[PDB]
Amino acid sequence: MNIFEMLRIDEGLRLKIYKDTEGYYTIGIGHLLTKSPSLNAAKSELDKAIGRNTNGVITKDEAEKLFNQDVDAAVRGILRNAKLKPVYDSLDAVRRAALINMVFQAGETGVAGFTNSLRMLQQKRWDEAAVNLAKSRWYNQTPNRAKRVITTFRTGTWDAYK
Ligand SMILES: [Cl-]
Ligand SMILES: [Cl-]
View 1 (cartoon, protein in one colour):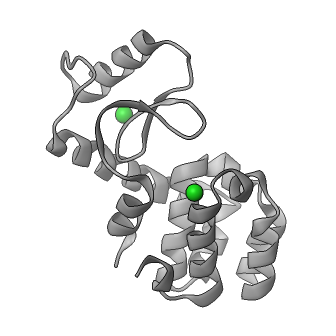
View 2 (tube, protein in one colour):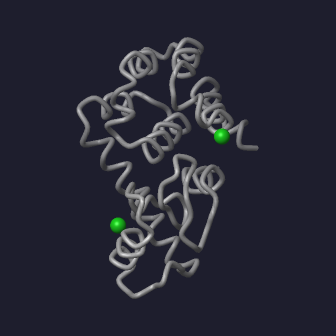
């Protein structure tokens, strides 16, 4: 198990424009296109991301390419974040993957805002961080996914994904 397979599990794969759980325009493996209500604005962002007139549909390869870029961006965003880098450097390899997963889903600002939980993670107080991470909109809106992420932080194994 690694970050790519983990996220592929949590986000799925769709070759056609679709709405995420919040109702936003998305494509591929969780690649948010836009937060605007317009399908057209979405088609436009897609074409621009792919580099061609797509018509709301992409190939598997295209999807995997967006995916690789987004995982890369997530990691780099963590290292560039003053609040995130420290937690991340403190963690083992599995737990690091759980951090990247939250980041990829909720944006860096998003995560950087879980102040108390980040502190708990850094202190290695697993069980407490889990409880604290659960008191969030993030958990309430996508509970089964959040649950997987949280177990990963709690245990340090890939058990929730196996
Ligand atoms: Cl892009
Ligand atoms: Cl869920």
